[PDB]
Each structure stands twice: as structure tokens, then as C-alpha cells.
Amino acid sequence: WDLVQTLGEVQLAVNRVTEEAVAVKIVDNIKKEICINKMLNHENVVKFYGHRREIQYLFLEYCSGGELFDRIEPDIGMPEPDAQRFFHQLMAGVVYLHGIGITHRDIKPENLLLDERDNLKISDFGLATVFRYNNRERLLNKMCGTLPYVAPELLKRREFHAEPVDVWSCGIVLTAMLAGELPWDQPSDSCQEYSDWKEKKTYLNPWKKIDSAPLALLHKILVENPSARITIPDIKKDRWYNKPLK
Ligand SMILES: c1nc(N2CCOCC2)c2nc[nH]c2n1
């Protein structure tokens, strides 16, 4: 395997005989990340091939599509139809992860990679952890992620359920896809932008730029009480989510 270039550490590696391409992760967490990656088998999660301990090398499906982040036009987002498709495949990824007791913990556009056909794949399990084992749920105490995408309970609680935090970060991604901007620096009362949302001031950016069907869903996802917040089974039955789009 020869490393043609740096992906953005991750570099593209092309096998000389086969000529097949891939992504190689070189890192000198990692033990957990490798362990969790070898559990995953889904068409919406970056594929794990193997690893070699020379400095550690991880062999991952290469997504020529690049980051979902680059498909978002600033201050504009992207065609509602494309966002819906991406969000559908994102739910598929997370349902799967959650179904095998795994939480990504850092869902964001930088970590949603697109393949040649543009199918979305969830990337980077360096922050991921088990939250269900032997059918026993474990609450999470550690703080992980990025501030704009983090659920508010993560800032306020000593302990919290894993699933609604991932759902919340998926709602922030949906907001970014349809408005081309992040709503708040962090999910806290001190923040003006977050208080404004809690007060339903949707006549402001970013909400101004979102049609009412998807906004109604964001209303159900960006709910401060992680217990009142919509769950993924419910998201599937959401009206916008099942709306035929051009
Ligand atoms: C395409 N792009 C990737 N990245 C984008 C740059 O940051 C690292 C992840 C990939 N990471 C693993 N496979 C990949 N295929």
C-alpha cells in the first residue's frame, strides 16, 4: 500500500497490485476505537478492513465523496430533497449503532463521509463507546463531542442517556443542512441564540430559512429535556421525514 495523499492522520492509500483505494489511519481510545470498529457491519458506517501495529495503522473504506460538510453551502445549506436523503441514511446509521449498544458521541458534518454514489457513512469511532451491554444500559458521565452539536444535558447533568444525545446532534446536522449555519455556539442558557430557540423565536435565523415541515421536526428534536425529546422510532413517523421530495 502506497499513500497517494493526505485525506485531512488519514491519507489515501492505493494498493499497487489490485490498485484498490482506501483510507489509512496512522496514530501512535485507539485501542477502543479499533475494538469498536471490528464490531461494525453496516452500509452507512465507514467500513473497517484491519489494522497493523508497527505507530498504529487503521484500514478504512475510502469515501471519494468527501465530507458532508463540503456539500453544505454557507448561509444556504442544500436542496431540501438532498438533506432528507442524507438524514434518512444518517438515521439508518444511528439506529444500527444504537441497536448494537454503540454511541458515536461526536456526530457532525466533518464526520459524515460521502461515497462515490453519495451514500452517507458515519466516520471516526475514536470518541464512540458502549452504552448497552448484556441488555444493560449504562449512563454516560464523561463529556465528549463538539459544543455546537452537544445536547444540553451533557453540560448540565452528572449523568445522561447516550441515545438522546446522538439524536440531538443529528438535529443540529439537519439544521446545518437546511440553513447552512449552526444555531448556537453551545446549548446553554447563557447563550442568546439558544434562549431564543427555547422561547420559540423562529422568525430569526437559522429557523427563518427552514420550511415548516422540517422545522416542526426540529421542534421535536431540539427539546431540552432529554426525556421529552423525540426518539428515532418516532422520527421515522414524522411528517417531513416521510414526505416525498424533488
Ligand atoms: C475519505 N475521507 C476521509 N476523511 C476526510 C478527512 O479527515 C479524515 C477522514 C476518510 N476517512 C476514512 N475514510 C475516508 N475517506
Image (spheres, rainbow, N blue to C red):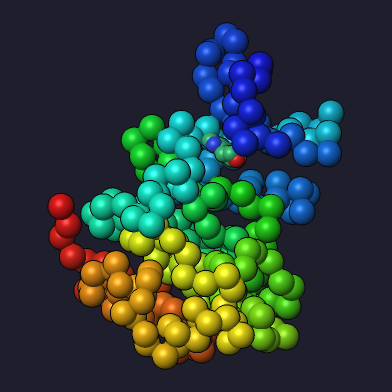
Query: Residue at coordinates 36% horizontally, 62% vertically from top-left?
Result: 179
Q: Looking at the image, in which quadrant does ligand 1 appear?
A: top right
Query: Residue at coordinates 15% horizontally, 52% vertically from top-left?
Result: 246
Q: Position of residue 121 (x, y in %)?
A: 47, 47
Query: Residue at coordinates 79% horizontally, 35% vertically from top-left?
Result: 56
Front one among 40 and 149:
149
Q: How many numbered badges does the structure rendering display?
A: 0
Q: Position of residue 27 (x, y in %)?
A: 78, 39
Quadrant assignment for the N terminus: top right
Q: Position of residue 21 (x, y in %)?
A: 53, 23
Q: Position of residue 215 (x, y in %)?
A: 30, 74
Task: Indicate left or right for 145 with 57 as reference.
Answer: left
Query: Residue at coordinates 55% horizontally, 67% vertically from top-left?
Result: 149
Single out the residue that lies furthest toward the top: 17
Q: Is residue 46 visible?
A: yes
Figure check: 85 above or below 215: above
